[PDB]
Image (spheres, coloured by chain):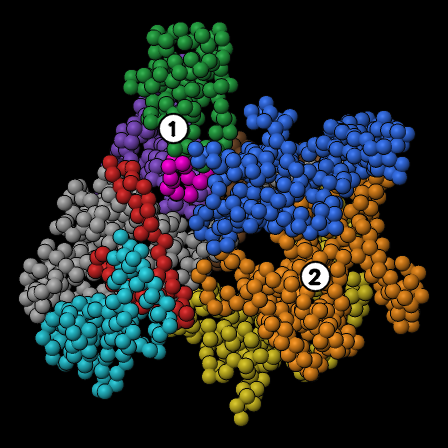
Chain colours: A red, B blue, C yellow, D purple, E orange, F brown, G green, H cyan
Amino acid sequence: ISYAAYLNVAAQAIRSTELQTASVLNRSQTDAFYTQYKNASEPTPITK
Amino acid sequence: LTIAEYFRDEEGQDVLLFIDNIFRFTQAGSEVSALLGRIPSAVGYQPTLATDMGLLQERITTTKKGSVTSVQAVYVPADDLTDPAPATTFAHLDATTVLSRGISELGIYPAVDPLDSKSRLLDAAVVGQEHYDVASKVQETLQTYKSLQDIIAILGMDELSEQDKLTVERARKIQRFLSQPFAVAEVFTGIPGKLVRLKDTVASFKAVLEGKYDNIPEHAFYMVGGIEDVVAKAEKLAA
Amino acid sequence: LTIAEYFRDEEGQDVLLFIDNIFRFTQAGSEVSALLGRIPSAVGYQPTLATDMGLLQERITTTKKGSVTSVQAVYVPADDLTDPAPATTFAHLDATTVLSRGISELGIYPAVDPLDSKSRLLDAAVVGQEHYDVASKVQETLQTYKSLQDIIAILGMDELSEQDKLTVERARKIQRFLSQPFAVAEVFTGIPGKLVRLKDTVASFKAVLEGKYDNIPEHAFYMVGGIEDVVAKAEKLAA
Amino acid sequence: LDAAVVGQEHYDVASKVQETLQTYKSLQDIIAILGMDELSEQDKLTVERARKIQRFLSQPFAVAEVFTGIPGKLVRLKDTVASFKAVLEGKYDNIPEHAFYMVGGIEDVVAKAEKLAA
Amino acid sequence: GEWFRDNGKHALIVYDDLSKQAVAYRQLSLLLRRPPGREAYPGDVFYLHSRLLERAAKLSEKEGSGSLTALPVIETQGGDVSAYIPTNVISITDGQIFLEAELFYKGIRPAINVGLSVSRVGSAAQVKALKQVAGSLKLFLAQYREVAAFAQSDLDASTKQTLVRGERLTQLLKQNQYSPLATEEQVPLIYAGVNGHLDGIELSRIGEFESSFLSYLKSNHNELLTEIREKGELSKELLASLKSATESFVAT
Amino acid sequence: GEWFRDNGKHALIVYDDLSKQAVAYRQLSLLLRRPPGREAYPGDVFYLHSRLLERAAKLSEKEGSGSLTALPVIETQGGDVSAYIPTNVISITDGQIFLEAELFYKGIRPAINVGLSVSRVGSAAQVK
Amino acid sequence: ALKQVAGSLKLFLAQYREVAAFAQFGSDLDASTKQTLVRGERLTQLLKQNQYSPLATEEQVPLIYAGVNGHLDGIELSRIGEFESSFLSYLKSNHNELLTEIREKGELSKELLASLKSATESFVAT
Amino acid sequence: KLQFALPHETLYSEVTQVNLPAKSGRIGVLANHVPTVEQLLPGVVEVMEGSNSKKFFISGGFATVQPDSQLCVTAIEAPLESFSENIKNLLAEAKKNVSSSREAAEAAIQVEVLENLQSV
Amino acid sequence: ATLKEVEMRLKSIKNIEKITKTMKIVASTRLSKAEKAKISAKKMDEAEQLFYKNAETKNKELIVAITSDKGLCGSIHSQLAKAVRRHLNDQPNADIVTIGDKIKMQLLRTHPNNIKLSINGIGKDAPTFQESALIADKLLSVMKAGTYPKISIFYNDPVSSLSFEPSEKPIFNAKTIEQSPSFGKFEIDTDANVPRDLFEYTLANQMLTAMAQGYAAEISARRNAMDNASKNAGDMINRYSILYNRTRQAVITNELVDTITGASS
């Protein structure tokens, strides 16, 4: 776990019923996916 | 017709009448009309289109003597459903299966346009409230999808909202679940004909609408019978 | 028309003639021609469409005795401005008055569209150089206001240049100043009616355009006659 | 326009030219509404080339001198065929469109291009 | 129908439908070899329908105050109101109730297109009680249509509110066939919708809402319904009684 | 106009406008029962105009050198220059000055559309 | 024989033009949508044909088999014309028993299919 | 002069004192502070304008006192009890039982943040 | 040509036009959200970045390209990819990580071997620290980011709402932070690796700063894009409606001629 990640956990525990607005929830949710690339083809897609 | 009328009245019993294609009746009427000294009416048809049709169709009826179940094939010129022939034909029917080209070019057979096909008997008082409701939501799901087909084009599938995406996803399945291998169509498919019972048809679609089959890929609904045939084709594809 | 004609021919009056609706005049001719066996012209109209229109319109005019001035309600088929019926009629119209739900919803009476209504006579050689110049900038101001409505709805009132934040404040006033209480509508309104002389109207607007009345609040422009009524009403809404 | 009558090379150039002109036409509407930026870099290239070919198809006529202001050009078939073949082979893409407009064969394009530099 | 109007009674006449009549009239004309025009219709086909439709009227006091009301039907082809006969009747009558296949399959039944419908008579024809609640409804839907396009994530407070009402008010106007409501049944429902008492209730339940709300009103508030039915107006007192009755029921 | 051409002087003729003339012409043709064609104009509506504008000419040395110049006016509908009558008269005249409604409303008057306007013979007659 | 090799080919091409409709959206695709887009584009090219040059069924059957069964999917599109007359030339010499079997039996036994499967794969690497 | 900033909202960007949960322990950065860089643990931050002070709870981040006496506090999340007991408890028991269920790395770090916030 | 044809083409555009304009107001709305993300990240950009100026920090290379997954936004992805390409000559042996598919597509057409990781499904909501930090966590792990002597972030810089500016900025590793000229201007506790933390925090942060500006730049481009789309879409509608009316009128005349010809005999 990287220092940024470490800080996310703390930051998103500082989140995880009101004061918990829309953009607050939607900072605790990421739609992102990573896909590794080589030679290009890939190493099959996975959630972040 | 005169033959089938005798069976209706003098054998006093159920007769089926199959007519392919009733359009040719009106068209043939057209072909002589100009020579019979008639000023042609709109789109070049005879001035007597509708009343000619009346005198014909009104004879093809069930009466207090006996029963006629007629099935008529109706050609629709240039695909235009407002051409006065199919246009005037509609009001004469109790149930109307409208086959569409759009549908057939997606490889859905039979190409029945699910929104435009109508029946006097789709009524809670006839099919029961459940049968009715399933049909209704089915129609709504598909129409929602139809409306949303232009946002699909410009802004991609991704730009849809929460419940809409799911509905659109449920539509695509339902759309394919309405396709069916006909026995007479076997040389066009290679697939054996399937005949589905009405109570299953309701049961199946009701279930799909409740999302009990959303983890099943699209190709499993296409050209199959009841619900069990989907479950079974989804394991043949998983294999 | 003939009734109006005699007031010009025998009393030498400036008569008004109202035709509601001129389109029904054209369709009626269309119908009669058809009935008389004449081969219909383009888009089904009579072949005599233009001379028929002439034979009416050319009788409406200034002579040396007086004038018949006709206000004719115009309906546009299919909203196709180029349909023979309007196309022919528009060849005789000296001007337009457009009453628009888009104006009456903002509470402006009469509901004239200040930009859609146009005149052939709005020209220096007909109205004088002054009259034209007031009207012109009155028209140019309301346009700049119209194209600034969209940024006011999303950004904010403060996102404008020195001269443009003044001219929206100016138009907003001009706009309310174009409304007028009518004399005949008093039975329904209770507000006594103003008949505003032309010289008044030119001078009244000329004075605002130079910016003599930016100190005046907006409500002093609503339902008033001359500029002397703006001076008067503003003092009531204070003291 | 048959590979036997005009020879395979002439035919092939003519076909590839028409293809390119057709792609652009197939896109006129997307280009018109959404503009060049919405196209795949493949199409972006085929369009940009089509736009050159189109201009290159123009020609100052001797009889039309009073309207072009430029003296007429007559271009020879073999010189025409070799010129377009070369534009297809992406050897002139780094050149401005206007250079292709209202000239003769390829040698005038380079000429107009070098002149319009200054 | 004119027998009634002429003897101080009131008739309603439904011509189902004048498309098919026009077609018949055309048949005779073409066969009698009368000059044909647009779509082969005779030059007097407008006069066929105006002659007819002008016979609906409300008579004066002197004349017994009788009345005939006409609901002609016209069948259009793929929505084309510019077709010859649709144009004739549309310009002859006092307004259109305009129906659509789209709205139909969407679920909106009756499939009335509010945008393209009107009564030119308007309010003078409407029970005051309804007019009072329906004044706004005309709007809350008009703006809903101008903004309906936005129902596809980043929507500010003002524009989302209008989306909530519109949805609900549209659902309120959904109606089962052969099930007309009484005016005193109608205004409560529209009162609830219009003023925002439905905004809370989730969309799939506005059906059962209308259903129970009326039966709860009959059980416990029969008096207000009766006052609406009999006096047709809403007094300031009634609005308050209605405001209370509604919030009361909404809470459960 | 021709008297001046025929006698050695120069006359200018303005037809305001031919559109309305062709409309007047179709009326007679229809009332005469001549088959309607495109836009219900008779087959010879082109001939109507062509025989007219052909009379605008510049005469040789041997004929006094008289000139008739024609400026026909045509009215388009919604700027459509593709209509039957417009293209007919375009195909008879030696060019056209096209006036764009878009420029005219903007204030640009004369509202000449440059691309769409051409004189076909003028250059060789325009003052050097 | 031709019916066999053209299994779902007409519908397959419909799936292709449905797929290539979604490509215009400037969209990147997955394993299912790129794989089919690629093959259809090659099948299209395979159906291009010069005038006055009709083919024999024994010549047609192989090419379609080579198209529908994946054997063209990794060949440059400008080279599909040259693949034709080269694959034909190759079968005429080396596998002339294969063609005679098709021109005379008009069908494909499991043995012919396996014999063809191998004969194609062989030619892919020249 | 103070520059306090979150990524979503920037709070300060003229102050007499600030108190930070730095590297090891709480600090108080006065008007003239020796330039320093310290990680901020997830804790409570206080800003002074005389004796005027608004506390903030913080995700953690970095503080730097500059050569020109400027402070730069940067964290992800920042009011205290007016913003963020049972709300935190239904997440704190979910962590102790998540250590025995790798995934156990992040779930165990959540507990050191919980019982720290619980002391406020 | 035929009324039925012209009816559908006119009605098709009538939708595209209402579409693009709905997406032009959806953009304008999302722009208030945009400056609350730009400004709030440009201020965290003065403060975070200032340490490095004073400490005077300077420096196989790792390129991180940032745009999005969504088109219809002018030349956002086109010219950013052009800035990366221009830079890529001066060192073709770079390793590329792509944030956004549209930019991945661009660089995959030109430098496919250089791309080693692609971050997906981005353009939707505004960029958050979680995405920022979890991408960072992937770079450190899968790309082994900490070992490159050079790391670069390419992103679009919104100068205004009318045009943008393809930009670049460096991310310094632990080694480089430590060894900087004025690193000993600060009383840094020499103990538990602060340069390590300061690097891995700045790796997430300056990515977010970049995304947050690129976002803003895109929304303001998409708006201007839709604005002209709607302008052209609407201008086409006028020309087609005009064509419609001609073709409508022509259909009435021609049917009327057939009927008149038929009665003539």
Q: Secondary structure at mark 1?
A: helix
Residue at 50% x, 31% y is G14
Give the number of callouts: 2
Which chain's residue wears label 2? Answer: E
- Queried whether the magenta region covers residue B221, the answer comes back as no
* Dot in front, 1 or 2: 2
Magenta residue span:
G21-34
Expressed as whole percent of the image width and height from the top left, the position of residue B115 reads 63, 44
Expressed as whole percent of the image width and height from the top left, the position of residue B168 reads 52, 48
Residue at 76% x, 29% y is B18
Question: Disc 1, disc 2: CB below 8 Å?
Answer: no
- Queried whether the magenta region covers residue G26, the answer comes back as yes
Q: Which mark is residue D17?
A: 1
Q: Secondary structure at mark 2?
A: strand
Label 2 sits on residue = E118
* In this view, E121 is above or below D65: below
* In this view, C92 is above or below B105: below
- Given the current orientation, which residue lies at the most extreme bottom position? C239
Expressed as whole percent of the image width and height from the top left, the position of residue E81 reads 69, 50
Expressed as whole percent of the image width and height from the top left, the position of residue E210 reads 66, 66
Residue G46 can be seen, yes or no: yes
Which chain's residue wears label 1? Answer: D
Q: Amino acid at mark 2?
A: Val
Left or right, H60 with respect to D104, comes to left
Residue at 38% x, 39% y is G30
